[PDB]
Image 1: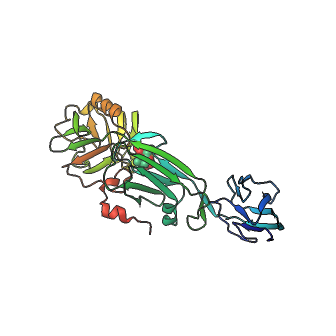
Image 2: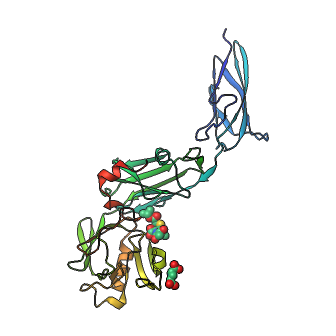
Image 3: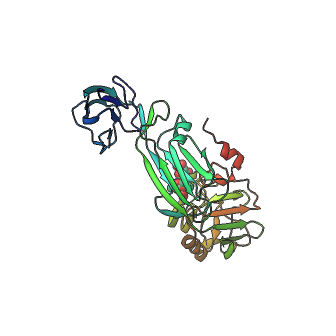
Length: 351
Ligand SMILES: CC(C)OC(=O)CSC1=C(C(=O)O)N2C(=O)[C@H]([C@@H](C)O)[C@H]2[C@H]1C
Ligand SMILES: N[C@@H](CCC(=O)O)C(=O)O
């Protein structure tokens, strides 16, 4: 008759044990009679034994900077075996928390990237990417691209198909993200792609045309950026919307008392770039809308058309600007992701 055998998922005396996974113990030639795991202060860790008695596993989050002692006994027809193991878990120098957009359960437009923003600079971008699990249904190829040292984006080659489910699991707890920085916790969000809404602003006509699943539903006269402060061409992702907002140029790097500075209260404002471009109500320029460009870059429309835009456009819908005297919106603006060529985006920038 054989003596039972105990096998744990950790080794006695180990250090740097990662807490991204549970601790387990298994028995062979016998069953587990008792397993306890305690903190250095003596507090027991929650765990559960399988019904057949062969496997025990922790069932609660294990802590950073802990010394745990595991005690296990197995019993079989051939006798008994007992082991005691002590190990230390990872000791981070820093913790970073991820924040994910869009919100859980949200319905968003066909331009919405997955966005994961860490509250600290990430030294090992590849480790962060490998810790993020994206599920799509219907499945579609996509790729990660970093906008700065803290925020990574994931998107497909082309705009999302309406009706797609997107699941984002940021599994960074216990993961070394470089230079001793570990994830503060896990985060999990899910969103769904709604109707295709693409609004095109053509400087040749000074009309902003809104198309919903390919059909024109609204044609709004607009006044875009004057020649000295023009609106950049390119693809813009719709962000936040405001019934009213004080637009402060200092938010976008321009002092208010400077030649192109401003501080202006506007109604019905939909943000389309981090650089400060909005679609918004402009009662002062209704005469120029559809005729001449007068703004600092914003898409001026009538009060009723700005309210319509606020009511009918959602986060992740698309505004495309064409034929202006500006350049192209930067790919790393924050809402300019689609201006990066797919070959470049797909290659990534983790290194
Ligand atoms: C994931 C992408 C697609 O969008 C979002 O994270 C939404 S956060 C929000 C927007 C916005 O209109 O989207 N921002 C600004 O302007 C702020 C910039 C200047 O820091 C941020 C903040 C107020
Ligand atoms: N708004 C600018 C300065 C504007 C001003 O000239 O008063 C800033 O504080 O960055």
